Every structure is written in structure tokens, then in C-alpha cells.
Length: 265
Image 1 (tube, helix red, strand yellow):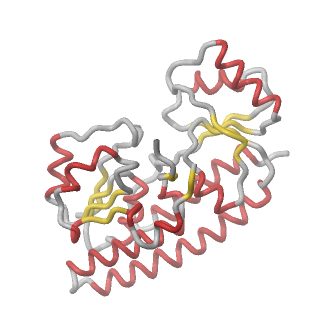
Image 2: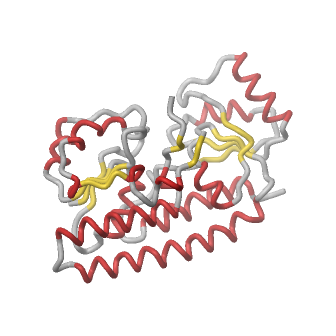
């Protein structure tokens, strides 16, 4: 099996290992990449895997140790890929590491995954070559449809609770006003809520986007009295099932959630 750290990384692997082998994920749906911790059973899935794929230390800190013990042939660290390095975006930690939101980086990742697997399974060279060409052409169109859907949305100001979308937004021309650091289970106190509210108004935002782990109480609260719509983004694709075209669908979903709140002047 190919073992991915996060679900949308699994989406990339899933497209390359389609037919050929299984794909597993370690971050379960509902958890955030910056607070998880490896179960003993998680560590066992790693050691016994054909290929491990993660973003790197600066992101899934919770995988440094067990990965550090695997030989190079068994591991793709996305942030360290030759072709990824020049695509890293700034904004201690200074490069943005939410990399599965960059088609370009997804493309390098599939190539690297294709490289490792084909070295191991050379009989399956044919299913894999086909898999790679399938992903590339599927991603290209998706990129095309998603550009079309989002371009009429340039200049529609939004805020997000979690500033994780930079790669996607730079790629598709979308324009984030900023971000607020909120719970997602405990409504903020009056000082903080007023500062957030003041900015939604001062800057006349159209939307404010939450994540699915956000309690609707917290979100509803922030938009109450304003004229701002409430949206939900799913950057970890918890709504999406692993499979050949999971990645295409992931980006599609994500653009609809943007569109659905942002559309409407």
C-alpha cells in the first residue's frame, strides 16, 4: 500500500496507485494537521508500507520520527522535491506548506510517486504510465473549468478563519481580505468579536469562510448583524472519498464552496 499523511495527498497517490495498489491515510477526517499524534497502530501502517508520502517536517510534524527511519526508496517528501522548491510561497516558519492546494505541486507529486512505484513494480509500468497521463489530463481540464468558474469572482472580498488557501487563490486569481484566528467550538468574547466585526464592516466583505470543524454557533455569531454571507471551505477534503479522480473532484468541490457563497452581487 501507499500511505499518505493527509487525505488530499492521498488523493494524488490514489490516482497513481489506481488498480496497482491500495492507498491509506493517517490523518482521520475531522482532525487538523497541526494537533494530531500517531497511534501505535498508525506507526505500524507506516513501517509495513510500500510507499510513504507526506509534505514534510514543517507541516505534519507528527511524522518526522517514523519516516526518518525509512530508506529513501520508500518515501516522497513533497516539500523537498526538486521541482517543488521553486514553487514554495512565502508568508518561526516562513514558507506556506499547505501544498496539496497547488495543482503544479500536485503534478510534481504524481511524477515523484510514479517514479517510486514504477521502480518497485516494473511489471505494472503500463498501468502506472497510464495512470500518470490520466491524472495530468484530468488536472489540466479541472484547472480549466475551475478558472472559468472563479474569474467572475475576482474582486469579491472574503475573510477566512484559517489562512490555508494561498496556493489555490494565487493560482485562480481570488482575493482574500484577511484571516481571523477563532476557535472553532467556543464563541469569542466581546473584545475579539467586535474587532472581527469591525473589519467585516469597515472593509465591506461579501463572505466569511469557515471550515467544517467549526461549530455553526461560532460562525453564525461572527456574521450576525452584518450583511456578510457565511461560507464553508473543506481544504482537507473530508467530504471526498479516495479513488482515481478524487483530486479533480477535491479541487472542484473547493471551487464550488467558494462560488456558492461568493456568487451573487
